[PDB]
Length: 52
Image 1: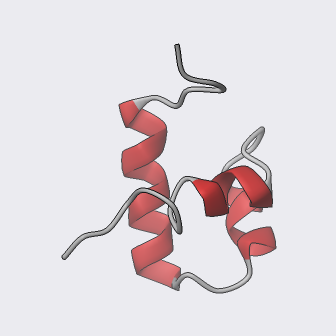
Image 2 (image 1 turned 90 degrees about the horizontal axis):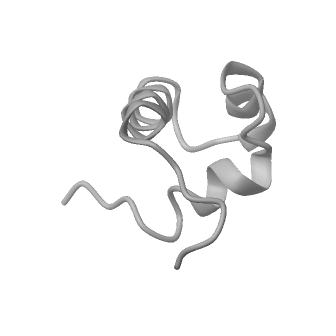
């Protein structure tokens, strides 16, 4: 089940970077998260994460 699943470590890391810098160019964020391409980083945010 699932596809290209992530890990809590990467989720937390991504969340921190996104909130810290901002949900701007995913290219810049991708540089901080090797292997996690801009598309994957975006998908792992503007599709699931939502800190209300």
